[PDB]
Length: 130
Image (cartoon, rainbow, N blue to C red):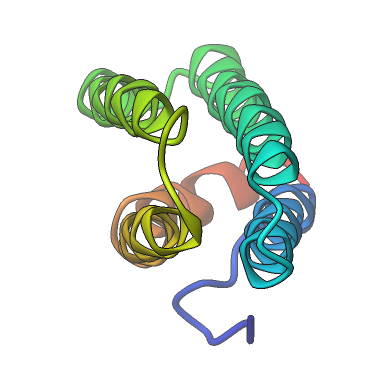
């Protein structure tokens, strides 16, 4: 996926978001090849990685006393909860269910990056974060 100005952010953050995009692409690859065991494998990995990327941002919020840390962490938390629900549907889902889930993942991620993560960039940049 492209990297518009809104999606853009701190280099180390761009690196992790792009990795989420890679996992998203891998998930589409599995569905495409109609491999549900691989799709479930990738989703699991996509899930753990998102939680670690959230934890990385949250650690930055802590380190630099980011004012809007509370709201942001709760948004992160709700999505994880959502990802866990989606995860159960893949147990008996088909390539179609994978694609619908994939669309939800994409819709949330892009909106989140452009509207929530973007709020912390200037703040962290002016404090020496990269």
